[PDB]
Amino acid sequence: NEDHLAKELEDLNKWGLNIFNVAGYSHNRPLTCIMYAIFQERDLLKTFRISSDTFITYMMTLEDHYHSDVAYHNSLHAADVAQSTHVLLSTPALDAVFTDLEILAAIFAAAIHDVDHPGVSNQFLINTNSELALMYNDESVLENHHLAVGFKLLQEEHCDIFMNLTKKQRQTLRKMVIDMVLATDMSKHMSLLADLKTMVETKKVTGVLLLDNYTDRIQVLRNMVHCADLSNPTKSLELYRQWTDRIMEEFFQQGDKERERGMEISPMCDKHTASVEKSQVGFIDYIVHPLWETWADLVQPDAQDILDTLEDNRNWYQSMIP
Ligand SMILES: CCCc1nn(C)c2c(=O)[nH]c(-c3cc(S(=O)(=O)N4CCN(C)CC4)ccc3OCC)nc12
Ligand SMILES: [Mg+2]
Ligand SMILES: [Zn+2]
Image 1 (spheres, rainbow, N blue to C red):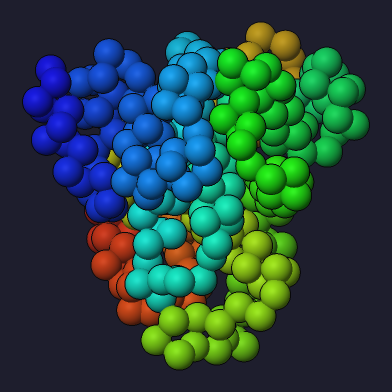
Image 2 (cartoon, rainbow, N blue to C red):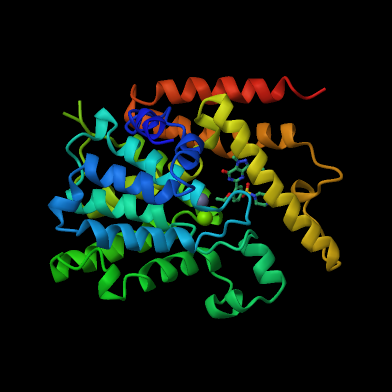
């Protein structure tokens, strides 16, 4: 259970990495593990002078703030999203486009984007008057929280992995990370899809994309991490079904919490009524495919592989409904 880990890590730069396998061969530290692997592969610890033991201790601690008892939003998902972002950042069509600071930001954001997630939605927290909804005034409650926890763990010197960055670089990195994580709030999905469509319709090239200013670059990065977040169904069917099983256990866990309390249960989180299979088809047709077809458009043909699989998996789930 150490050579197996290195064998699985050869696919670090591939969509086909199996994060459940690395979780198993890493003594259940998939996020610490994958984040160290990625930072080395990109020479980020050297480029930004991050001490290796500082990095390990931060990551072990960030990972410890992902809850083991939530089915989906644990450190396995942060790891999956970080690694998925790492791959999209290498898409040939975006080759030389982002600074190393922008690259650092995207990967760090992916790693923290769901830290301390309680396993319930923004809507539940708001309708139960939770302390978190009061803190954040019902706006992007969880996403604001995830950013707060992530940045709060940097406050201590033994853990400030951004210590040797310029003062200006910490401000831009912080502005960028805030922007990317807030962009994972699913109630911003349509707003993000619309803007991504506008950039496809006005795209320049060389065959590498032209992004004139910051507003363009961070708008791609927001959509990248959102795509990474919502990339489960574009993975090979074996992985996608494990993710489907996790997310649905979590959602049914929440509908049970809604039933215990007499509030109305949303059809999709109802374990007595809801079809797992039909809800995945709907999830794909109305959210995931519209988004990944557009991302595919922006980077074509780099993402055509992902789009075929997405479509294949979609058809597999459709033909599992009676
Ligand atoms: C119903 C789709 C189930 C599902 N499978 N997978 C793999 C995912 C996923 O990665 N994300 C989400 C997801 C969906 C919404 S949703 O907007 O489609 N939606 C809100 C209203 N409820 C009642 C249902 C879900 C909101 C947040 C999510 O995950 C955290 C980012 N759902 C699934
Ligand atoms: Mg989230
Ligand atoms: Zn997420």
